[PDB]
Amino acid sequence: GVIVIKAQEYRSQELNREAALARLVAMIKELTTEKKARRPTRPTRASKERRLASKAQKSSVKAMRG
RNA sequence: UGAUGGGGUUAGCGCAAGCGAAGCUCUUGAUCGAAGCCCCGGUAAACGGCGGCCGUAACUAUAACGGUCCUAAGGUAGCGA
Image (cartoon, rainbow, N blue to C red; front, side, top):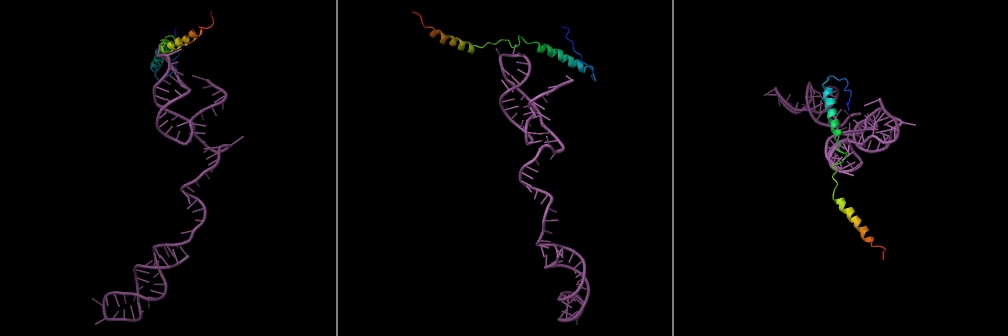
């Protein structure tokens, strides 16, 4: 994790300061990725749908017995 | 090409003055007038040229997509330090 990059030649060294600076700073941002898409914010609308989806199959299992 | 009108000079009409035929001049030029030009299309293995801005998907990251502007058209196939 010695994370290296060669901020090569320029007409002002400080230019690559702000270059390598915004590079590492943003790198930390890009590597924020809190589980790549995970908040996860799992809605409740899809939960009732599948729940009622389990309901339809429930009553049909009133099939064969006795 | 040359219709006209306009200027100069001077028989005759007239004793100043003036007028002015006619001649000849100077000038104006109506009119005639083709291609080109304009309009019109076709033409890119003719010369050539072949975009912006901005938002958006289960926080993250990108944006298939969406909005709007602009252009004659908005770079496909393939390829790419």
